[PDB]
Length: 364
Ligand SMILES: Nc1ccn([C@@H]2O[C@H](COP(=O)(O)OP(=O)(O)OP(=O)(O)O)[C@@H](O)[C@H]2O)c(=O)n1
Image (cartoon, rainbow, N blue to C red; front, side, top):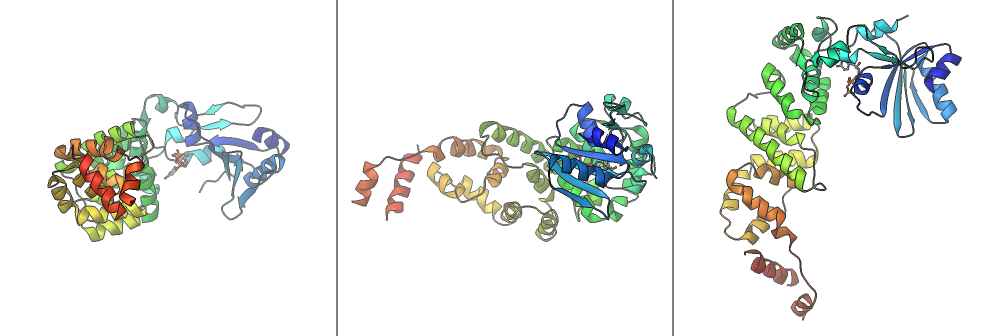
């Protein structure tokens, strides 16, 4: 599609960055990013045209978003911020993000590796292009680790020292907060997110990020324990799933104050029930686990756990004692139902009698 228009336009168009990586590693992505030696916006406009699909150009920035099918496309004009592709690439973060694939019909299919992105790709390694890089875009500090987390990669040695420097230089602080919180967000959407936390703690990045936070053993314990819990509840109920990353985020801010914590979650654009989970854990959780343990009958447990959110329950499973309790609630007590004739006999106040029959049959 693009290669042919680039012929008609006599341009050169390339697939660039993570997408390429995702391809070499065989991930599927319908979000595809290009860099153009030529006018990108018009290439986009003609692609859209011939497909007859709506396209949004961005004249100021010089890019265009357009969506072919459920597949998404963003065309960007090459820039050094003319510019050779190698210039567009050399400004990027990591070797494995620095590659490109030709849609140009002559070299079509070609992986373009200047900095050894493929070499470094097989070697399972996070390597920046140049050493100033961290200073250039400090958010990368996380992304690096993030990559290393998701794909199980090691930092380049030089990269390692570079990163510890940058961290230590508190660049992590002086970077605009918005991009950082953005990153942390995208980090906690990860399946490998725990390993990312391993790297976080390793470089102590979080201490340069959130106000008043530091790491303690118990936190880590309950974090791993959380991974077990999430593994399990994800296994049993496939329809009951939530985005679990938040939990771990929460587990970090637990020892923190409620003021700075809720400020931080609102800062994290945490969903309502998330910040609500923060509030309920900060305030009434002690009484919660107490009266949960103070409940002798299965139905009392039922009446205690009903109004509350699921994530909160998942958080309540961390205590060894309450494990079998939550197991009973989730697998049994909440599964019990009722016939007709009896209801009609209670009808001859109703919900009273129903709650009563609940209390009666549930205890065993
Ligand atoms: N802080 C950043 C953000 C991104 N990039 C560059 O931006 C491109 C893609 O942006 P991004 O989507 O953030 O990185 P991806 O590798 O595509 O990973 P993902 O799709 O998950 O975001 C890559 O070439 C990368 O080099 C960068 O150099 N520094």
